[PDB]
Length: 242
Length: 225
Image 1 (cartoon, chains in turn orange, red):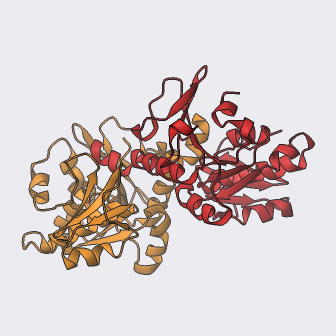
Image 2: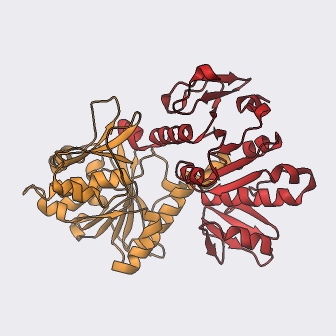
């Protein structure tokens, strides 16, 4: 991942990007995307295109309170009034991580892609500067790495989270199912079910297929969005309740 | 990737697998795939199914790589090694790159077994496997044994997907290949498939239901070929 560091880039930005395996370039590449560190923001650009992508949680809470269709059921899916800790295994741009943290939950947001993790990190950094989003941003802990591969070690380190939240961005044929995304889904769900203390929550399109082709214990259905909930391995549905 | 090592696994197999970041397991996983090392073979399995995937090696592309010039070829997307073997069959020395641990392990074992087989020994000896991401390993290999004559490629929120997804990986792959090859970068594509990384090639070879877009190294004058 290339990163163009403009002369106006603040010291905060310069220090932040230094923690990511990026490749500083003196000019934009001839093709494709690259990161741009200008002023006090890190953004992602596409050569030849004006529109960019930036993580900005300023209107996050507002956008959430106004969303309909089922996405607003995320709070009930993780049982937010129980004050659970949550590991967001597919953080990406952090939309859901910020929403969860805004409910008062302590979130560990996993993101394995260098560019995306950097974008998210800067978004959290800027969120801490705004008095209206400071408290929430402080409850978001970025974990730069692959969740399936690193959750087991983190469990031994700081204990199991109450909730593991998943929202994959996907919703020779036989061979591809064995080594491709299908297999990755199997491993992610399995690892999440060995990790969560209370539930593994998976966001899905209304008619979306079940993650790893596995049926959940119960679901929270909206019009166009739903949440599949799996109980941790060895949990007795008789004791558990929702 | 999990690997179940049966007690019958030969030392040749036990040695081969040590080159990959595989997770040894005492029993198959609850669900999904895993590698099985039994007797003198490494195979891929799916829990619940009786079948198994194994690499067993027992003219359009020839022109695309201009085999007549007997060029060295680097297969940046080796996979199960089908095209690596074909290229090697033409008498060319091939260096195959594969980044997936399971796929790489399977290919490595197929090459190893092919060497033990008379009718494939000659061809298999011309295939060298390199584990890792091509975009990353090729530059490092260049500084070692030098540039190859040809780099062979055969891969396979919207805006966001294009910037960090497969679209970007394509750009990186082609760019690196064009900086590695000394003569040509050959890309396999379906009959009327779209251009890789959305870039136009210098020329191409259209076959029955397949096509090969050919790019030239950076700073190359097409008029000289």
